[PDB]
Amino acid sequence: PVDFNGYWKMLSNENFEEYLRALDVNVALRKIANLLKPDKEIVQDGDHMIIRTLSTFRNYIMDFQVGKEFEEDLTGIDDRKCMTTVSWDGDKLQCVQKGEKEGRGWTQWIEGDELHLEMRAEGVTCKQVFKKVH
Ligand SMILES: CC1=C(/C=C/C(C)=C/C=C/C(C)=C/CO)C(C)(C)CCC1
């Protein structure tokens, strides 16, 4: 396990448009979303974690307990509900989102002062990197 606490800004984004296409997100929103460089505020307190993907255009908030399955309301992305579980896999943070879509989930880890995040859905993989600014 590692410590994700902090405020992070996006450095890079790769294959995000195809990842959103796999979720049936409309073209217009896909183009707009891929041009946004959202911040990430993570509050880690024990096994309780809050991850806020921030943008004035639109936000997405996660508030969960590691190891405990919860009903994830993805309103704002594709408006789906998934039975999600986020667990530790060594120093990596694994998330599996069970629902209508195949292979939906993500993996997060740290390299120096950078947050690495890979998102997957329907066999598609998106890669993002963030820099710890606070
Ligand atoms: C579609 C869409 C967006 C998607 C956000 C996503 C897919 C966030 C995933 C966050 C995760 C996995 C956080 C855990 O570290 C954002 C809000 C950028 C802008 C508006 C359009």
Image: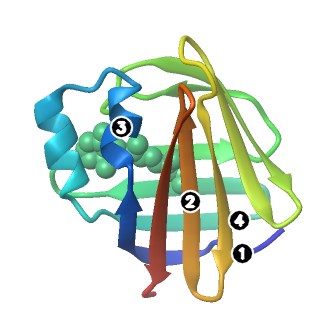
Q: Quadrant of the C terminus?
A: bottom left
Picture residue at 79% right of the left edge, 35% below the top: 68
Query: Of tags 3 and 4, which is closer to the observer?
Result: 3
Question: Relative to 110, is 77 on the left or the right?
Answer: left
Tag 2 near tag 1, CB within 8 Å: no
Residue located beneath label 4 in the image: 45
Question: Relative to 30, is 88 on the left or the right?
Answer: right
Residue furthest to the right in view is 90
Q: Residues within 10 Å of mark 2 (few under 14, many from 20)?
A: some
The kind of residue on which mark 2 rests is: Leu
Query: Of tags 4 and 2, which is closer to the observer?
Result: 2
Q: Give the numbered dot on residue 49.
A: none
Mark 2 and mark 3 lie on one chain; the one further toward the N terminus is 3
Residue 60 in view of the camera: no
Q: Residues within 10 Å of mark 4 (few under 14, many from 20)?
A: few
Residue 128 in view of the camera: yes
Spatial CA distance of label 3 from label 4 is 34 Å
Query: Of tags 1 and 3, which is closer to the observer?
Result: 3
SS for callout 4 = strand
Residue furthest to the left in view is 28
Mark 1 and mark 4 lie on one chain; the one further toward the N terminus is 1
Q: Is residue 107 above or below residue 20?
A: below
Residue located beneath label 1 in the image: 3
Residue located beneath label 2 in the image: 117
Residue located beneath label 3 in the image: 18
Closer-to-camera residue (129/54): 129
Q: Quadrant of the N terminus?
A: bottom right
Q: Is residue 83 above or below residue 126?
A: above
Mark 4 and mark 2 lie on one chain; the one further toward the N terminus is 4
Mark 1 and mark 3 lie on one chain; the one further toward the N terminus is 1
The kind of residue on which mark 3 rests is: Glu
Spatial CA distance of label 4 from label 2 is 20 Å
